[PDB]
Amino acid sequence: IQDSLSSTASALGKLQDVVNQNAQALNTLVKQLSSNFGAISSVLNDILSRLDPPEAEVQIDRLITGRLQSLQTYVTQQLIRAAEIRASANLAATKMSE
Amino acid sequence: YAWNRKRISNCVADYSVLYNSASFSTFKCYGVSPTKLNDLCFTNVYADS
């Protein structure tokens, strides 16, 4: 078993997949900050620096809606994944105890 | 039908004077507010007459 662990790399795929999934979810959430969502620009500072409040508010609201939706999606996915990991942890605890 | 296009680049533009000039009956800005024009940098400006 020591030799197998030293040689083969796909042994810990179960943990590597969890790490990769979390990293990819964070990367997608971060990349979602670069979307116009229909606004003139994807940069809040640029929007604020070009229009008066009454006109800026529309673009700001578009960006707010888009980013709120992105956060909600990310949090729901995280909740489901956390439930799966909790099931795995319960199985691991039972395996330890028995 | 033969509108003339002029190039404006490599200079400092003081839009405050233009905005304050009452001689202009209509002064409408779409992608940028008039007031903020004094605190922005543009790659190049096209003036069509």
Image: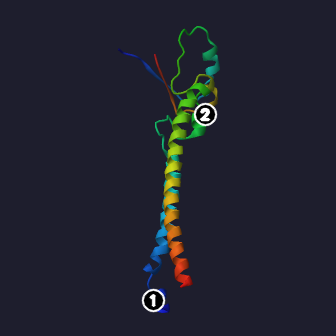
Q: Secondary structure at mark 2?
A: helix
Marks 2 and 1 sit apart, C-alpha to C-alpha, by 58 Å
Give the camera-side residue of A73 and A60: A73
As drawn, A88 above or below B2: below
Q: Chain of mark 1?
A: A
Q: Nearer the viewer, mark 2 or mark 1?
A: 1
Q: Chain of mark 2?
A: A
| Residue A52 visible somewhere in the drawing | no
Q: Which residue is tagged 1?
A: A4
Q: Secondary structure at mark 1?
A: helix
Q: Residues within 10 Å of mark 2 (few under 14, many from 20)?
A: some
The disc at residue B38 is none
Residue type, numbered disc 1? Ser
Horizontal arrangement in the rendering, residue A13 relative to residue A75 (left or right) = left
Question: Disc count in the image?
Answer: 2
Residue type, numbered disc 2? Leu
Give the camera-side residue of A60 and A87: A87
Q: Position of residue A8 (x, y in %)?
A: 44, 84
Q: Position of residue B11 (x, y in %)?
A: 59, 28
As drawn, A48 above or below A97: above
Q: Which residue is tagged 2?
A: A48
Q: Position of residue B47 (x, y in %)?
A: 49, 21
Q: Residue at x 42, y 18 (%)?
A: B4
CB under 8 Å between discs 2 and 1: no
Q: Position of residue A64 (x, y in %)?
A: 55, 39
Horizontal arrangement in the rendering, residue B14 relative to residue A70 (left or right) = right
Q: Residue at x 48, y 54 (%)?
A: A28
- Name which of mark 2 and mark 1 comes first in the sequence: 1
Q: Residue at x 47, y 40 (%)?
A: A37
Q: Residues within 10 Å of mark 1 (few under 14, many from 20)?
A: few
Give the camera-side residue of A34 and A17: A17
